[PDB]
Image (spheres, rainbow, N blue to C red):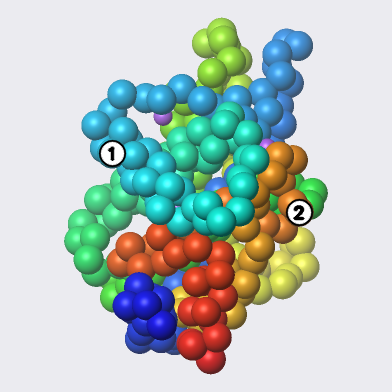
Amino acid sequence: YSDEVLGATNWLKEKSNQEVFSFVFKNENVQLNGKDIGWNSYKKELQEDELKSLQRGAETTWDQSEDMEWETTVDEMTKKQVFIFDSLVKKCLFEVLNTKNIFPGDVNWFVQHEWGKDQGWHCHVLIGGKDFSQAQGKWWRRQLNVYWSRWLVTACNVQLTPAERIKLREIAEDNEWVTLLTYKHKQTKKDYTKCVLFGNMIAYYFLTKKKISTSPPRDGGYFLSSDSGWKTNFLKEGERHLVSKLYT
Ligand code: NA
Ligand code: NA
Ligand code: NA
C-alpha cells in the first residue's frame, strides 16, 4: 500500500465511469520498390523540442517502472522504437487537442504499448473529457490518422524517394493505421463509435497484462504505459496488479 499504488487506484476509481474513446495506433509492413518498411523502421529521433521532451518522458517511465529484481532482455532497438512511438502518438493527440482548443487538464488519457500475437507492436489510447462527445469519434480518428501518417513518414529511417514517401503516407491513411472502437456491425451498415469506461477498462483489463521482458516479446504483453495524471507510469508489473486488486 505505497502512496503511489493508493494514489493510482484512487485516481482511476474517480474516473471509473468516465466515457472515453478507444483508439489503436499501429503500423503495417510495407514494401516499396524492394525496400522493406517494418514495424521498427521509424527510428529517426526528430529534433522538435516537444517530441524530444516526450521521448525523454517515455525513457524515464521505462526506467522507473523497470523491475531490477528480474533481468530484462528486451532488445535495445525495440525499446528505442517504442519510446519514439510513445512520443509520436502523444504528439498526435496533443495536435488534435490544440485544434479543438482543449486545455490539457480537461482531458483524461491512458496509453499502453503492447505486442499482439498477430499484429505485433500497437498502442492503445483511451481519451476523453468534458469537451468530448461520441459523435466526434469519426472526426477524431481521421484527424489522428492524418497526424500519425505525417509523423511516421517523417520518422521513417528507410531512405525513400519522394514518390515512395507519398505512397507510404497514403497507405497509412487509406489502411487506417489509427483505428477507433465501434460496436460490431455489418460491413455495409452504419458504424457507431463505442465509448469505453476509463477507470474500469484500465483496472480490469490494461493493468492485467504481463510485462514484456524478452525479445521476441511474449504475445499479448505490454511494454510501457502512461496516463495524463502520471499515475500508472512508474508502476512495476506487481504494483499494477495490486492496483487492480485494490480497485475492485
Ligand atoms: Na522522432
Ligand atoms: Na523485440
Ligand atoms: Na506510454
Residue 91 in view here: no
- Label 1 crowd bin: few (<14), some (14–19), many (20+), radius 10 Å: few
Asked whether, in this view, residue 130 is left or right of residue 122, the answer is: left
Task: Residue 210 in the image: state x and y as whole percent.
Answer: 66, 62
Task: Residue 247 in the image: state x and y as whole percent.
Answer: 48, 87
Disc 1 on helix, strand or loop? helix
Residue 143, compared with residue 157, is above or below; it is below
Q: Amino acid at mark 1?
A: Ser
Instruction: Return the residue nearer the eye: 214 or 107.
Output: 214
Task: Residue 6 in the image: state x and y as whole percent.
Answer: 37, 82
**Label placed on residue 221:** none
Residue 116 in view here: yes
Which residue position is annotated with label 1? Answer: 53
Which residue position is annotated with label 2? Answer: 219
Asked whether, in this view, residue 164 is left or right of residue 145, the answer is: right
Instruction: Return the residue nearer the eye: 123 or 58.
Output: 58
Mark 1 or mark 2: name the one nearer the start of the chain. 1
Residue 171, compared with residue 133, is above or below; it is above
| Residue at 54% across, 18% down | 157
Q: Spatial distance from mark 1 to mark 2, Cα to Cα?
A: 30 Å
Q: Quadrant of the N terminus?
A: bottom left
| Residue at 24% across, 32% down | 49
Disc 2 on helix, strand or loop? loop
